Amino acid sequence: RTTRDDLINGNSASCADVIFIYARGSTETGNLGTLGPSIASNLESAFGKDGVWIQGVGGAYRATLGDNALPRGTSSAAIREMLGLFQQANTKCPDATLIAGGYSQGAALAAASIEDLDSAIRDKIAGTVLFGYTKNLQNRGRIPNYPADRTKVFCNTGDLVCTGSLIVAAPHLAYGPDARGPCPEFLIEKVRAVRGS
Image (cartoon, rainbow, N blue to C red; front, side):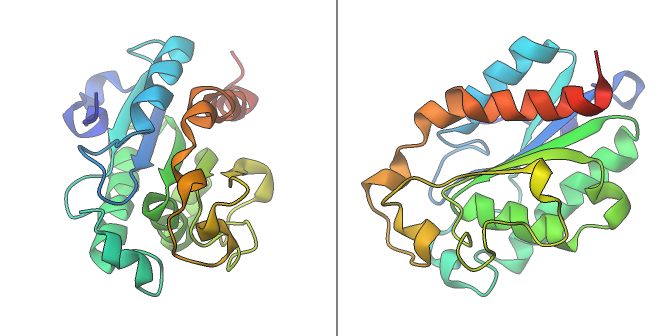
């Protein structure tokens, strides 16, 4: 449901082929929030329960609304938490293909973490999805140091956070359909592009 710690709980002896690390939006519950569960279910359908590990960013990431105003769009502690998860994935399952995603503050967190990530690990992320990307205008729809072809941004018309503001309007809460279809579609495609099948 809203909490998944497949990576942390997982046995190194039987690593999944795909590891998905996701950061929730502000004030959302568990470590997956409102959109994470939908993405997870679809990933499981494609790769099978044992084929993919779903890991939300919990720990120090409190998804505090006020942190959207900090320089990177989230807290330093949150970035360290997500970086640590990528590092854990790399160590626990070196042969797994990674995919990532984030919504709202989680999107900023995903961008910041990926930017700071060691290139060797960053290069293992076959695709990243960002919903209501709070740094969309500032970063010109990109994630620093990460290829455009591996990036997909879902920014609704009227979603003010995609246009340089921190105002939360109705379109910012309308990403359900995207999380159910195009998002997993993109992630699956990106994984298959490098892993074949």
